[PDB]
Amino acid sequence: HHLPAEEQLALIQRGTHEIISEEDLLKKLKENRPLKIKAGFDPTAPDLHLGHTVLINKLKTFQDLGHEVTFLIGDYTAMIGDPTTRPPLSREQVEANAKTYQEQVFKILDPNKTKVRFNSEWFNQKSAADLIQLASQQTVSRMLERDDFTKRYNNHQPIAIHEFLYPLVQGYDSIALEADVELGGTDQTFNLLMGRTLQSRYGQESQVCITVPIL
């Protein structure tokens, strides 16, 4: 049934830019169970541009190999706006943009074998105290190590503080999903690594991080 793990790893490794501990990936595949596969998408764009194709085909490889792909809509942070200012996304915009993503993605993935989820599902129920707990798990110095934060800080461009909370949101999504693997583009390394780090801090086995080219 489940392919030998050495062969799974050969099909997963092709076309990828980096795998953070293949030693951890091989161990998960040798467990011979459906790994939970997380791929997150911001719902602001009108569609997925054709540069996502490699990424979606890699989710296809995971699903063909028997693992469970979760297609995650990061709607929570996009629907929060300013206190009384340009507005945030309505729910109507999230649901309409996500519908277009799904019709794109399901020309490749099987809908009966893919989970579609919105991270407001757990995050609507989180209190302010929950987010403070989360925020205590990372240092300001590590957040400023992200490339986009490093340039803005040195070019003396303001970084609002909630921008430091968004990667913590993405990392916790991994805990809420019990992700075994999370995929993203070459430039998402920092954010993907956040879930691997937070998971250990919450008592979970960590995820493997896999990057592919997003053209």
Image (cartoon, rainbow, N blue to C red):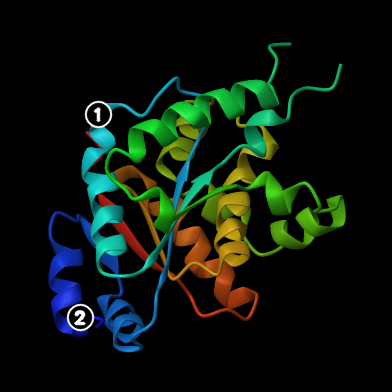
Residue drawn 56% across the image and 77% down it? 200
Residue drawn 51% across the image and 59% down it? 194
Residue 158 in view here: no
Residue 29 in view here: yes
Q: Residue furthest front?
A: 112
The residue indicated by pointer 2 is 3
Q: In the rendering, at what x and y percent does residue 205 appear?
A: 51, 80
Classify mark 1: residues with Cα within 10 Å, few (<14), some (14-19) or many (20+). few
In the picture provided, is 209 more to the left or to the right than 212?
A: right
Closer-to-camera residue (8/86): 8
The residue indicated by pointer 1 is 50
Kindly state the secondary structure of the residue where label 2 is placed.
Answer: loop
Q: Is residue 93 above or below residue 190?
A: above
Q: In the rendering, at what x and y percent does residue 195 appear?
A: 52, 62
Q: In the rendering, at what x and y percent does residue 8 appear?
A: 19, 74
Residue type at tag 2: Leu
Query: Looking at the rendering, which quadrant does residue 134 occupy?
Result: bottom right
In the picture provided, is 139 more to the left or to the right than 123?
A: left
